[PDB]
Image (spheres, coloured by chain):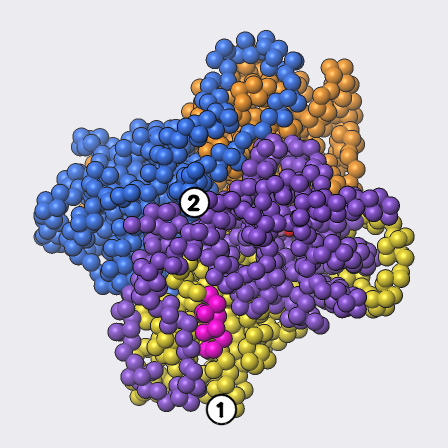
Chain colours: A yellow, B purple, C orange, D blue
Amino acid sequence: MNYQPTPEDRFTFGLWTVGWQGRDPFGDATRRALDPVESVRRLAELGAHGVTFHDDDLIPFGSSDSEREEHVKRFRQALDDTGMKVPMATTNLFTHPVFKDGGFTANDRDVRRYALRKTIRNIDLAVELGAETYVAWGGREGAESGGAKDVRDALDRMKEAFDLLGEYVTSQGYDIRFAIEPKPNEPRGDILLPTVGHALAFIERLERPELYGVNPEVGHEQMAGLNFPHGIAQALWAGKLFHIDLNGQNGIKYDQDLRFGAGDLRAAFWLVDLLESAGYSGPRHFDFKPPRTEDFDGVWASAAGCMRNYLILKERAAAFRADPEVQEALRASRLDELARPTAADGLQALLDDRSAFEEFDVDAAAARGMAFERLDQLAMDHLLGARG
Amino acid sequence: MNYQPTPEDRFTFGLWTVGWQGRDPFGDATRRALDPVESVRRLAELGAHGVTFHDDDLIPFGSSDSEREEHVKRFRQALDDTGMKVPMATTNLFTHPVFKDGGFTANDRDVRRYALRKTIRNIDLAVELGAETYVAWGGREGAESGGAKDVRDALDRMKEAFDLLGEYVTSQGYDIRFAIEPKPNEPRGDILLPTVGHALAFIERLERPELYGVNPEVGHEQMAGLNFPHGIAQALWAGKLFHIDLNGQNGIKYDQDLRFGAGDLRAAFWLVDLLESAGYSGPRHFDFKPPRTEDFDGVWASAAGCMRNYLILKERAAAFRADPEVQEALRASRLDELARPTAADGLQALLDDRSAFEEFDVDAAAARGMAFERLDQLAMDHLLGARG
Amino acid sequence: MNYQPTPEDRFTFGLWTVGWQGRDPFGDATRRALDPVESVRRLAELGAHGVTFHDDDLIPFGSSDSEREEHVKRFRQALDDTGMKVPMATTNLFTHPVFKDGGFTANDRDVRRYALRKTIRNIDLAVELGAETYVAWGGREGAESGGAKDVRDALDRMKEAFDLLGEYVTSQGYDIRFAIEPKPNEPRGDILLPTVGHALAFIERLERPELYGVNPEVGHEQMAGLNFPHGIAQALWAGKLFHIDLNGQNGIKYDQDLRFGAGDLRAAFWLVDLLESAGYSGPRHFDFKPPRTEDFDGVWASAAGCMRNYLILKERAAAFRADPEVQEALRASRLDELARPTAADGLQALLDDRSAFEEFDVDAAAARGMAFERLDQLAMDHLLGARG
Amino acid sequence: MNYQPTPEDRFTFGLWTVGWQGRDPFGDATRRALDPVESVRRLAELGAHGVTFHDDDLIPFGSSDSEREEHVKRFRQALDDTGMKVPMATTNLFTHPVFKDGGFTANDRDVRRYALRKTIRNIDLAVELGAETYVAWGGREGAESGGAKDVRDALDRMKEAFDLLGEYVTSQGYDIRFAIEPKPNEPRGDILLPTVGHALAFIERLERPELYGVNPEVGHEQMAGLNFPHGIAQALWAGKLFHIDLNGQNGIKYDQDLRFGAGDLRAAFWLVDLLESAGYSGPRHFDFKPPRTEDFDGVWASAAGCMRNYLILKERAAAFRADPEVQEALRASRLDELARPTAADGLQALLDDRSAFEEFDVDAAAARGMAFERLDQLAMDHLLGARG
Ligand SMILES: O=C[C@H](O)[C@@H](O)[C@@H](O)CO
Ligand SMILES: O=C[C@H](O)[C@@H](O)[C@@H](O)CO
Ligand SMILES: O=C[C@H](O)[C@@H](O)[C@@H](O)CO
Ligand SMILES: O=C[C@H](O)[C@@H](O)[C@@H](O)CO
Ligand code: NI
Ligand code: NI
Ligand code: NI
Ligand code: NI
Ligand code: NI
Ligand code: NI
Ligand code: NI
Ligand code: NI
Ligand code: NI
Ligand code: NI
Ligand code: NI
Ligand code: NI
């Protein structure tokens, strides 16, 4: 009944989320800029565990070394005063006009080198602040037209960039891992490594694959009409879910970044069920934007809503899995059989097993119902709190 | 000017394409069944190089060993009489009611074993006929609801299945490779390994990854709103493009399987440009369905159209790449720079290079236009044959 | 707490829903055909109010007048024995190969005439059985290619068809109205009158517009990524919501026809809220397909689930609207102001009102938050039954 | 062979198109602001016929009456010096924070009144400059959440707004018509009157429907996965195509506003074919955004490309329709029959016609192929300039 979050829940927010001023492609900002220090304080009061940042969220682009030092000290004091942590950091390689054709895969070589130096500089800061994960979102890596980018060459440049970052981390002896955040499009017509699958495949071609994982975002996969929980399951199966971005999205359209729980509610339920049952111990990070219709009270209400929805869904998913009637239904649908090896007896045994082919009664097997609808209605009843 | 195909062009068609009777979710068949022998003859006359098949296209499900032998002999004679090849074969693990919850990942263990035996049986036949690639399309592997399938367990079963097939091939000393064909949905609500990326990632977790590649289909990736040429480039980059399915699709909706060239025409141009420039030497396979509005003359016109469109696009892509004005435009857009290493000088050299950060003039770099629009209009002019 | 349906709830089902055999584009039927009489009985036991039918669901295509009479008598007796009603009927102008290019807009004139006669014949039967609404779903009206159909001519033929049906109804003195059911695509590449909006616009060009309305289906509008509740609101605003098809759909892809409640759950909540608050008194019709993974027990579980979900959502929507805290939030968000005329004072008064422009403080107005996030979280809490 | 535009072609551009600075949701501007006077001159040199504007593009928001007068005089002189016309004008009711919840349908009544006064003020200016059409794009009319907007009330407010504008125009004796521009989403989660169909339906409920039409945009309808040429055909059929916005879009995602010709090339061909054959005499207006990767030379290249592509497509569509082999194919596909009335003989004659039902040979009719594939390949050959 009580859905109050505590820092033990590991809820985190990016500074750019509650700090989003409301500027969109067709309108000016509707809210004044927030001082990172005020955000840290406000979030701590709501029950958050920590915050994340892009280098440029914390230190205005173009800042001198002294100003940079000042901005960091103020922030550090706010963390000390609240007990807030900084589990992840990332680089802004998308806002400045110089990154109009990308950062790591920009056609101009000088821009690619600059991108790497800007990233490395923030990796040092991230480590200093205690971050365990460093996220990379290649928002500008891609194209609007076919001849503008040779994708094979671009992937060589992307691999070269990540390999160099791995070499840097290893040489400095840092205890930090990278997580690639996929997105299919926006702001580029098509973005490279568009989904969790493409990102996972790419990671296997890096020199030190063990240092890289993925940071999937619910809305991003939904922008390609994909099943988010399924994508997360594949990431977990590969042992690559290093971090996760939680939010809401209503189908295939622009990236809405609604508060978590909004958008596809049932997908949110299945996501929470999976994370909790798989024992994901990383942060529950919200990358969302409080709609521009809201004033400051609305941004804090929206932020609180992210955490509340996760906690309600967690309760309902747990009740679902603990319900004896559901456990019975899972057996009726043969989920237990799905977990048993198809042929632990081996290939030869399988080939010699007449019950597997020559004497297999296909019609009898075909007539068995899967009982998935009853199981799904039990899930619906639990989600809606209408069990009886 | 002449766009006549010859077997040298490597165009192939599945028996199920020109043989599609026109039955859809809301209507009965509009065409009579075609005898595979007649299809082979008709295709040979059109200039095709070969045909492909699912076990059930060639041998009616439930056929006795004698009938099976008869069906194969007739087919073999047609191949001998025409000079047609069979470069690829696949298994039908989706039509029969027994596969309603899948083949390799069905919840019922007995069905999974049956699926493997049915596949192995057709692998032997494929080798006998000279096929070099064996395709697997897990059309029924997936779900309509969240609790019906634990994806981690399903992926274990999928890996187990492919590992066993690899062991079989290796033990028999066959010279055949596997290609996984992804599809995001339809006929299941969500299909496992939904895109080329997910398939590539999965392959890296198999015991013998070198035996597996992908068989992407233009319409399938477009069903998720993805850029097909980009996906193919990633597959080539990984050295995994073993085969390809060519067709047309108009956006995000049901799988239309229109003739190649129809649907997204510009994507078709960029695809051909990529395949030809990368030196893809595999078959140019068409997996399409002549619309049910057509009679038999219409199916052959549609089939001929697939090949004609590929040949026209090939001519235009070649003219584009050979045009000195385009080569100049590519340099203006720095495609040459994209192909040069970002830091062949090494990490330390990069960190010490003041021109890469401390003295980098971001504003000057930012002011350079990419000239992508002029380049894209040159591509448009070439596609439309309006160069001057 | 009790969500048991009674015939008073007006829940109806098409014979083709629970009777769907499971045949899809890639597979054969998984269930045996149901006798309409058994369906009527089974539905009555579940608490349904009535059933609907296509002519061909009730009388096999090609039936002689005697067989036709027999099929109708049996059905009629089942209705009498159960108390079930038949509030709506429709024509199957999509299954038979003759309708491959359409019914009312087929290019062949003889087919268009046949389509009209087949429809008229079933209108007589519908009236005999007591149907008040006659639905028309032009599933085959459309095209896969641009030159195949001149849309202006096709719309002339569509208007001609509906005008003739109106003349027939009027001349016979029948008390029955028509409802056009839109769908954007599938089985045709693009279907004419693709959304509720296009259908409403078309109706205004008919000779007797008062006889025609719309029969929107949740999944159909969602196939175009549209907001279903918004579409229904426009239909109600125009006084054209004559009937409605309830089901579930997971985004933009093939038409899934999942049970109501599945798919976009929040959209389902807002739909129910709107129907109940607007006083829609027509039938709550379910046009869904129990997944082919199910046996007969599963189809009845799925059917029961449709009604259960509607009843749960009705309870939650009512609690939401009755909550004093929500009523306060609605005022905070100025929903009360939205309902007040912008300028009941008139045009001249508006032009002379300096507070509306010359002395309007745009900055003060701009600074007011809309408080939509708090309102939406109150809606979420009510839906999930987590109010406190 | 020559594709040079002349003012006779009626090509127009909005000031906000070539003047777009490149600011998107994730990045700052990449180009400096253009002075409207320079845009008029540059466009005139390219062969454009005229320009269009939003009030705020021409007169900075908040300008005093004197500055306003100055800005208008400069603009007027540029028009006089070049011969450029201003056929359409519109209001910016989306950029300023005050319109965060809409203009005509904002929940706050004072904002709705302000919106009307701002619009009326620009209508006077539009008439002064000679504009014949006044466009309204309700970009902010809509919502991100269900309870934020009661759609029935919002439509009452929308009708009230348009009715008042009609009364104003009529009372002043202006010769100007309105055109509503639909868009399904972005910047709002869902926008009211999302498609051409919804807009057409709404127009029929206004007090003076004859004063209102639609201004469809290719990319907007494609954002809902709809067939643009089909939508335009419905608009023409109703006599409501008052203006049109030409651009390119690659499927269902954010609004790209690519140059015309880019995106769905075949849809562009069918659109041009329809406009030219139907005798649309209104302006060919381009509402596009030169990608932010471009410098100023790139924006002019992109603008020129819009016109070039329209002219090439016009040539190809005309050659297609004039080709005797195509005319023969159109008859083979019975397009001539589609244009003939289904039953000019009348209802009674139809009911008594035994050839229409009792003696209709459905099987013979069903066996006729439509020959749509050959027709479509002839269209493809013409588009690609590969006829022989
Ligand atoms: O869409 C944008 C991305 O998700 C971004 O906000 C962050 O996650 C990392 O930059
Ligand atoms: O959509 C279906 C698939 O593409 C299939 O037809 C073949 O490629 C392999 O079974
Ligand atoms: O998708 C199909 C349609 O919705 C159909 O089943 C019925 O509503 C009317 O024929
Ligand atoms: O997407 C935005 C709209 O199309 C807009 O730019 C103009 O047409 C009218 O404001
Ligand atoms: Ni994001
Ligand atoms: Ni996002
Ligand atoms: Ni993110
Ligand atoms: Ni396919
Ligand atoms: Ni396909
Ligand atoms: Ni295929
Ligand atoms: Ni339907
Ligand atoms: Ni449907
Ligand atoms: Ni329906
Ligand atoms: Ni637009
Ligand atoms: Ni647009
Ligand atoms: Ni526009």
Question: Which x, y percent locates residue C284?
Answer: 62, 36
Q: Can residue C60 be seen in this view?
A: yes
Quadrant location of residue D165?
top left
Q: Is mark 1 within 8 Å of ligand 1?
A: no
Query: Can you identify the residue that label 2 sits on?
Result: B1
Q: Name the residue at 70% across, 54% down.
A: B89
Residue D97: name its quadrant: bottom left
- Residue A316, how many percent across, how many down? 66, 61
The quadrant holding residue C258 is: top right
User: Which amino acid type is shown beneath numbered disc 2?
Assistant: Met
Q: Are marks 1 and 2 on the same chain?
A: no
- Image: magenta residue range: A151-161
- Residue located beneath label 1 in the image: A172
> What is the crowding at mark 2: few (fewer than 14 residues within 10 Å), some, or many (at least 20)?
few
The residue marked by circle 2 belongs to what chain?
B
**Can you say whether C68 is above or below C249 in the image?**
above
Which marked residue is nearer to the observer: mark 1 or mark 2? 2
Q: In which quarter of the image is the N terminus of chain A?
A: bottom right
- Total labels: the figure holds 2
